[PDB]
Length: 83
Length: 82
Length: 196
Ligand SMILES: *[C@@H]1O[C@H](CO)[C@@H](O)[C@H](O)[C@H]1NC(C)=O
Ligand SMILES: [Ca+2]
Ligand SMILES: [Ca+2]
Image (tube, rainbow over all chains, first blue to last red; front, side, top):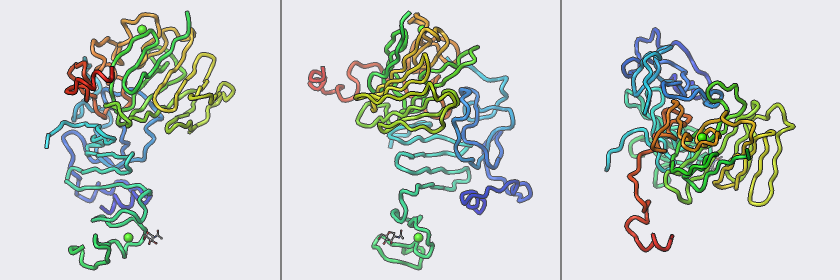
């Protein structure tokens, strides 16, 4: 709560969970980033840049690749199609 | 009473999931509410409601000494009878 | 070949360039027309954002953002608001005549807005199978206006439009069971006759 406060007051603070020995819980595959963007490019998204210029947000997201597809992380090669 | 799926967008409210965390945005009405994985609640609220709102999250002036304006309109010191 | 014209006839209907009315009620933000399609370098990207408009009512105010020449001019609440001026300001041109905001953006692009709901982007021969979106591709063929983002035709328009949403994590609008009596004309046959 102290971190989330100081971020809202206009000072984001990084890497405080590396040694704190308390990882905030998140589902399988994703781990707690700090300051991730809300418009994470997923597997069935349009490549539409310089539009999601919202504030940076705390939360958990997939690894560097490993895009999102219906509440899990999967590598971009295994992206499905939709019909 | 009817259980509905998610996402959901009715009536100016977008019930979504951002960054693993559930979100309920009401930017037309002027609020954003999200719950995290541990169950902790959070409410972001616009400056339109400055010293206007009151409730369990108090009012939105700057002073913290007067966040206990009861529903009767009086101050308090015990957090509970508030 | 003449100039073509999209349209947003009412709250939830769209008339393609080649001419195709279809029903798509949505509440997310959608690509109405863009030149960034396939192997094109591309120049512009027009979007349309509705809110509370899955059910047509005195709700459903539309917002429109248009992205051209590095610009960002958007509009809602009966007014036009620039957010980022574009480089070649010479082609930018606004005409506030009558019930409408006419809005010129180039030799072959234009927008016409009645300040409430109707969006009529006008294009010329210059493009001619270089665009795509909810308005189609402007090629003369009317049967291929439902080619989605994933490069196939759908038989159902409600699955076509959800291909063109801008945020992948907002809601997919639901398949409504097809009825001639939409919402309030359903049980009241008189109000279905007074409306006719
Ligand atoms: C906040 O609103 C109340 C309404 O009665 C007013 O009395 C008070 O002075 C306001 N405080 C400020 C300075 O905004
Ligand atoms: Ca206070
Ligand atoms: Ca066509």
